[PDB]
Length: 108
Image (cartoon, rainbow, N blue to C red; front, side, top):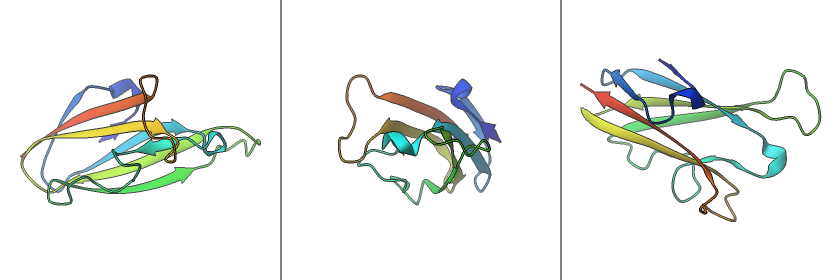
């Protein structure tokens, strides 16, 4: 249901059609955000799962303060689907020190 950085590498057992909410700290003032490979918020495969994403600025409204990206992942097919995100500047792409997040959605 509700997935955070704490769940990195975890498998969630879900139904096809079930929405999985992933919440990750994200600070757009860094230029970094969470992306699928290629630097998009779009699902790598719409047939496998659908992804919606929203940034929530911090309640504090403090300048430079990080907020939270929420990804709503809806599994569309049975199987174990890797939701593979990387915290990167989309103009830079990933590197060996990029923060990464993965959750597996074991779907039926």
